[PDB]
Amino acid sequence: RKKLKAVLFDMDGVLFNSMPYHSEAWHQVMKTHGLDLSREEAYMHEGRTGASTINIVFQRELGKEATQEEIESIYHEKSILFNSYPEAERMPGAWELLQKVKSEGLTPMVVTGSGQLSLLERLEHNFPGMFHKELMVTAFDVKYGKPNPEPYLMALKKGGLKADEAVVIENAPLGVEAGHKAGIFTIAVNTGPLDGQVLLDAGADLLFPSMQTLCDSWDTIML
Amino acid sequence: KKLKAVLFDMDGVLFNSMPYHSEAWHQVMKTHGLDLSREEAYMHEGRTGASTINIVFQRELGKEATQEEIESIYHEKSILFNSYPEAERMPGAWELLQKVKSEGLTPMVVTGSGQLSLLERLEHNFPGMFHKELMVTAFDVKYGKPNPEPYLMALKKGGLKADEAVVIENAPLGVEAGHKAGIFTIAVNTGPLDGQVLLDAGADLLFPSMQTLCDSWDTIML
Amino acid sequence: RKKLKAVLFDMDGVLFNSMPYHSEAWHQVMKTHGLDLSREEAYMHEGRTGASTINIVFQRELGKEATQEEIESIYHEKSILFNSYPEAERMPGAWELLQKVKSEGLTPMVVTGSGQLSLLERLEHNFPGMFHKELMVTAFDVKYGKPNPEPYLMALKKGGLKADEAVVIENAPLGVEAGHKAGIFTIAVNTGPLDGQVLLDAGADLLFPSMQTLCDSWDTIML
Amino acid sequence: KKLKAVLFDMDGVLFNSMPYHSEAWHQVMKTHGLDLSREEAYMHEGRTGASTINIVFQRELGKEATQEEIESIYHEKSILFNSYPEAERMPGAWELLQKVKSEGLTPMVVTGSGQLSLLERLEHNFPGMFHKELMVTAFDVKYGKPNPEPYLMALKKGGLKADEAVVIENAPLGVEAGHKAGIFTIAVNTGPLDGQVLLDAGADLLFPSMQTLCDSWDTIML
Ligand SMILES: [Ca+2]
Ligand SMILES: [Ca+2]
Ligand SMILES: [Ca+2]
Ligand SMILES: [Ca+2]
Ligand SMILES: [Ca+2]
Ligand SMILES: [Ca+2]
Ligand SMILES: [Ca+2]
Ligand SMILES: [Ca+2]
Ligand SMILES: [Ca+2]
Ligand SMILES: [Ca+2]
Ligand SMILES: [Ca+2]
Ligand SMILES: [Ca+2]
Ligand SMILES: [Ca+2]
Ligand SMILES: [Ca+2]
Ligand SMILES: [Mg+2]
Ligand SMILES: [Mg+2]
């Protein structure tokens, strides 16, 4: 596009291959509490904040919301379990795509409702020189999280951008929904186990099978 | 069955009010230079007025509406809605309520509506059916559909567990709220959307109208 | 409707509760031949003639069509297995609905590509006085079968009817597709294990959960 | 990989001919008092001319077209199609073919088209790529897409099993034919339909264009 200034990347399943760990950790911590959240459902709910994920389960199974102390207790258990796995590595193609974006004079940004500190603290070491602190959105900015467009709208505000000056790179239907409802052109990369139809149904303007094929295709789609 | 209660949505289930709500949202947004189509208003059916306004601002302006903007637009919408000849009952709603009540079940209303003209007409339209203590309205909720909050609140007011209730809904966000509350949810497709959207939202059954639901009730509850 | 003259009923899963048997028999006969057709896939393919069902499997698994002698051999094995089960009983609500249709001066018809003779020979005993021989479509009329609209168009021709003078009652997505592509108002009854969305996606104008609820609702929908 | 061959559809994959086919079908049907929209012509992409004509007759007239009707309508459609400036290559098709050939794979064409002007331009557009003995056209088939017949015939002509080939298709009925042949099928969404329809038909991968497929080929074949 001719108007493009910024590329807004989600983190889990776009920059880091972290979803096998998040899905396993959510499934196991819920099971420890006698609550049912399958690994597949964890993928379906990918994009929600920790508080929202916990509340989905509490609301359907226990008929109430979690209290804040329950949210914090369960999230801390989930985070400990996530961190017990060998640390998540970069999605293949992410670094190469970021280099391309930057070389073209575009501003990369990260937009996530993650509170998984061990990942956030590794962004610079994994993608050196790509991201600016003042141009990032994390759990420490967000009140609602995806699928609310709030995090992407916050990224636009931080960047001094209009929606038509950005592209979102997302991999999960709730994350695509947030980008789309922010009015931003959204590219889905199907890096999980779900059908690509769910990404398109959520509003993705393009769909690719992987970050590496997006990288391979980037110059063509931006022409 | 351990069925004890039937939780009815109001707009498009008890009253034929959606042609009016969709028109009024479309028109008031148009007055403010914002594009909200009648079809889109149906897609948003279920949300509170404040949430509806915010979502349009988020997409079209890249920001949340201010509290002032929400109050002003909603005030205009309510005036316009009430300028139409008052909404009539959905055919079949009263017959179904008599059936439910005759079977010893407790009718409840669950809505994020704060439309006083409709809420204060419930008793006159469905005499003896509903009680303020057994209703959830805009005045009870923080989030509203599609959050299961209002249905969970109704369960609590009724002293119910989710497996003791059935929800009757007509809109995808409403079906989603009932389903995410863990409650068996029957969709009645009383609007212009494809029924697939109601099933996709988690409806356990789909009927084309309140009258066919009424006709079919004793069979499905066997 | 004010134009309605005829109601065109499918047989399997609408008049007879025969689909648990057809699906099991197809699955088992294919397994005997070292071919994969799941019970769920048998439901997905409900509506196809025997030759078509066999060819779906041969084409995807063996890279060719079945010969006619193979089709007849395998179909006869399937029919023997189907007939080894206690004979299929009426769908609850079918007889009551047919009585209603007839009392309203509508002409009931049967439209099926089934060659399962044991069911066809039982139609009169199960629904006495409802159907006319000259106003039926079976495997012995059809060249292609559902999802081709051919069988429903043949029913219209036999009945001296225009598409707008009939209603189809179907329960399977390929059968709904045939009715819809014949230009006929089609009511789906979800009497199997599939999602109702598949019936609606195929073109059904109404969807009910069972023959008994259709029966309960018939006078309302025809007003 | 035991990959040996790449089976290309023609219209909307090798040539940008679908704006012309859809317009010509729409117009010729209109001349005969039959409603076939341009969008519907895209939905039917893949079918042989005879099948396309029959389906419209079945829905609108309640009968099959006669052989005479099929021959007359098809004759008119072919004349109209060829009255447009001849269709150009899909960007990326030639580069992809060079890549495929360089990797030792056998290109094939699989189509129910009998459009001689396009079939007889294959060699001039893609020199050295294709051979008549390794093609399937309208002149080979009894049924055509979405029956897997044409893909199965291509496998046979190439001495292939289904696990030794990849199909490149752009239309839902074409994807369906490849998938029902048991062949890995890549959809390229080069028309106006939603990509969900291509995935619903059984595509294993979806790309937005022939050029992005070309760009991505070496990565997906790793
Ligand atoms: Ca993600
Ligand atoms: Ca949503
Ligand atoms: Ca999967
Ligand atoms: Ca789309
Ligand atoms: Ca409603
Ligand atoms: Ca509609
Ligand atoms: Ca369902
Ligand atoms: Ca059937
Ligand atoms: Ca079809
Ligand atoms: Ca099921
Ligand atoms: Ca429909
Ligand atoms: Ca094509
Ligand atoms: Ca389109
Ligand atoms: Ca798939
Ligand atoms: Mg949702
Ligand atoms: Mg098909």
Image (tube, coloured by chain):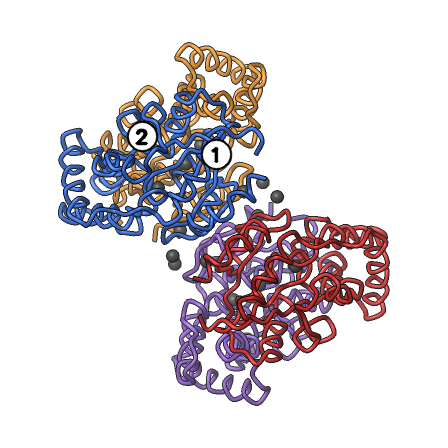
Chain colours: A purple, B red, C blue, D orange
Q: Is residue D215 shown to the viewer in this render?
A: yes
Secondary structure beneath dot 1 equals strand
The chain holding disc 1 is: C
Secondary structure beneath dot 2 equals helix
* Quadrant in which residue C94 is drawn: top left
Q: Which residue is mark 1?
A: C167
Q: Is residue A142 shown to the viewer in this render?
A: no
State the image coordinates of residue C101 (x, y, percent, origin top left).
Answer: 46, 36
The chain holding disc 2 is: D
State the image coordinates of residue B28 (x, y, percent, origin top left).
Answer: 82, 54
The answer to whether marks 1 and 2 mark residues whose Cβ atoms lie closer than 8 Å is no
Q: Residue at x 19, y 33 (%)?
A: C66
Q: Residue at x 27, y 24 (%)?
A: D133
Q: Residue at x 35, y 22 (%)?
A: D138
* Quarter that holds the C terminus of chain A: top right
Q: Nearer the viewer, residue A28 or B12?
A: B12
State the image coordinates of residue D135 (x, y, percent, origin top left).
Answer: 31, 26
Residue type, numbered disc 1: Val
D92 lies above or below D138: below
Q: What's the distance in space between the residues labelled 1 and 2, CA to CA?
A: 36 Å
Q: Which residue is mark 2?
A: D150
Residue type, numbered disc 2: Pro
